[PDB]
Length: 106
Length: 106
Ligand code: HEM
Ligand code: HEM
Ligand SMILES: [Mg+2]
Ligand SMILES: [Mg+2]
Ligand SMILES: [Mg+2]
Image (cartoon, rainbow over all chains, first blue to last red; front, side):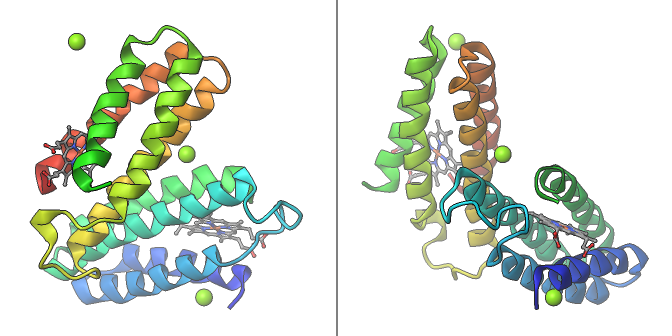
């Protein structure tokens, strides 16, 4: 899957976690967002096509995703304990990384 | 070095930044710090030895460092812009991150 597909998989699943009632739904959604994130990371965004492999940017965007996966595990750890609400909440913090990094790379 | 040294390097250098009066000292300290972090991140803390690298824990431990590294980077950039005060101020935010993950794994 490509970046356009990765982001799409992310957006959709964060939606699902909103409409989610039971724990499981929330888990399968994150499992998916964690896969997508890592993949997205292995990619090179159109605004960085020229940027060098180790450009400070390439390191920034890189780290960004590590923060996203980090926050996904946070909510994943919770969905696992069966704690919906808490995960759903912890899942919102993700919009903050989205905005912070989109602002810089979208 | 071992997790005992890396942290030594962090506690040592962090304080250096507080007593420093010019950007230069700050940047050098932060640079050393950034290293130590990436290093501590690669080791397994005693309290987590018998754990699995896929364990919820290792993920949270993994993340903490990512948070810290990002913070060292945000203060490092300010120092490269000569904001000795804004830089030190940012550095302060590191403690918050330490007290938090030390509670869980120290
Ligand atoms: C889970 C939170 C996130 C959501 C819901 C999300 C959602 C989206 C959506 C809907 C798009 C538009 C895709 C299109 O129009 O084809 C997009 C694009 C993009 N996102 Fe995210 N995103 C998230 C997190 C991130 C993060 C953390 C990064 C960077 C570390 C990132 C980097 C990008 C980039 C570079 C694009 C533009 C792709 C292109 O130019 O085709 N996104 N994202
Ligand atoms: C840059 C802010 C930090 C400072 C100044 C700091 C400082 C220290 C100091 C002085 C020690 C005691 C070492 C010893 O007694 O030998 C220590 C231990 C430790 N720190 Fe940090 N630390 C920081 C951040 C972190 C973070 C983010 C983590 C999260 C993984 C962490 C995890 C640990 C652990 C697990 C130990 C115990 C080592 C042991 O006794 O085996 N520290 N830290
Ligand atoms: Mg996908
Ligand atoms: Mg004092
Ligand atoms: Mg940053």
